[PDB]
Image: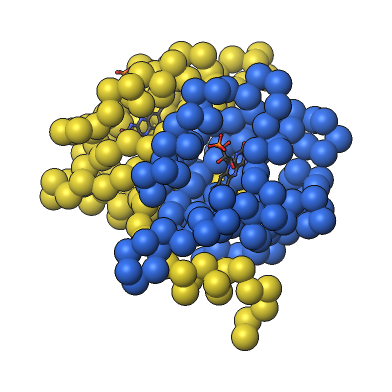
Chain colours: A yellow, B blue
Amino acid sequence: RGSALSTFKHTFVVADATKDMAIMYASAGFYEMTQYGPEDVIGKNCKFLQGPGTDTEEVARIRRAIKNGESHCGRLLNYKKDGTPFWNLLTLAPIKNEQGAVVKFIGMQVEVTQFTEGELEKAMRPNGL
Amino acid sequence: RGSALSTFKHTFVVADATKDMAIMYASAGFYEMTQYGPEDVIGKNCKFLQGPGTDTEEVARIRRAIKNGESHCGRLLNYKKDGTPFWNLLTLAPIKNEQGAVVKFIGMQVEVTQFTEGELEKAMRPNGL
Ligand SMILES: Cc1cc2nc3c(=O)[nH]c(=O)nc-3n(C[C@H](O)[C@H](O)[C@H](O)COP(=O)(O)O)c2cc1C
Ligand SMILES: Cc1cc2nc3c(=O)[nH]c(=O)nc-3n(C[C@H](O)[C@H](O)[C@H](O)COP(=O)(O)O)c2cc1C
């Protein structure tokens, strides 16, 4: 779901389009998923998460989305502070003013884990039994 | 966020990998976003949403994800029952048994709308003021 949003429940960052898309904000979930702290993250471009085997063509689609002011999603290999790799389903959306110009982007990250048959059944079942 | 999941809050479908990826389940949000009903959706492949200008190369990445049993996200133009186009950020994840084989896929759809500066500030602000 997502794109109400909550800085305490959800994993997202906000980039300043006035500032070469530097991170100007990160949610609690971001620090928790990546293991980085505000002193590492704020003011940096979010590509410090990228590393060996990060797909160059997915990065290029992200870049084009950003350049065009479009929403976008893509799967990217990323790395936590301790070097652990994870798959990140990254959702991006532009934020505009009234002038119709992009002032910021929000990126929502999802760390892919295994969804098992058991947990899916519970979601599908329309009650609490 | 997403990939607990709720059939009443979230927009998703579940496909049966035993059945040429026919939809075997759809959430309340799916029927509400697409305007289709269970009598249209259940048993069909979800490409009835695709239409003019749906990107062929995004569809091909989805197909490859499905074939490889990988999670995936991508932005796809889709159409509601009344013909209205919408951008769908589609997230896909495989569901496996214990044998380690893919029995189902879950797809979570997000209809892209405008995120405004005002609603973003409220999300970022760490309180209810
Ligand atoms: C709001 C936002 C969030 C982003 N989050 C991530 C992220 O979680 N992981 C990642 O690898 N790249 C992320 N990116 C992409 C990188 O910051 C960067 O835009 C991409 O690598 C292209 O950089 P370049 O054009 O300088 O090469 C994000 C971008 C934005 C605007
Ligand atoms: C669980 C699941 C959900 C899907 N949801 C959507 C959807 O919301 N919109 C869409 O255009 N395609 C969706 N697809 C993709 C199509 O069903 C189909 O897999 C894709 O068009 C490739 O079809 P083909 O290999 O038969 O050409 C979904 C697929 C799965 C497995």
Q: Residue furthest bottom?
A: A129
Q: Residue furthest left?
A: A82
Please tell me whether residue B72 is drawn above or below residue A35 in the rendered image: above
Q: How many marks?
A: 0
Front position in the image: A29 or B87: B87
Q: Is residue B99 left or right of residue A35?
A: right
**Residue at (21% x, 46% y) in the render:** A85
Residue A107 visible? The answer is: no
Please tell me whether residue B52 is drawn above or below residue B64 in the rendered image: above
Please tell me whether residue B53 is drawn above or below residue A123 in the rendered image: above
Q: Residue furthest right?
A: B82
**Residue at (65% x, 38% y) in the render:** B47
Q: Is residue A78 left or right of residue A21?
A: left
Front position in the image: A49 or B38: B38
**Residue at (44% x, 16% y) in the render:** A64
Instruction: Tell me where residue A106 appears, x and y as whole percent.
Output: 48, 34
Classify the position of ligand 2 by quadrant: top left, top right, bottom left or bottom right.
top right
Q: Is residue B96 left or right of residue B62?
A: left
**Residue at (33% x, 22% y) in the render:** A57
Front position in the image: B81 or B101: B101
Front position in the image: A49 or A56: A56
Q: Residue furthest front?
A: B19
Q: Quadrant of residue A54?
A: top left
Instruction: Tell me where residue B17 appears, x and y as whole percent.
Output: 51, 56
Residue A56 visible? The answer is: yes
Q: Is residue B89 left or right of residue A73?
A: right
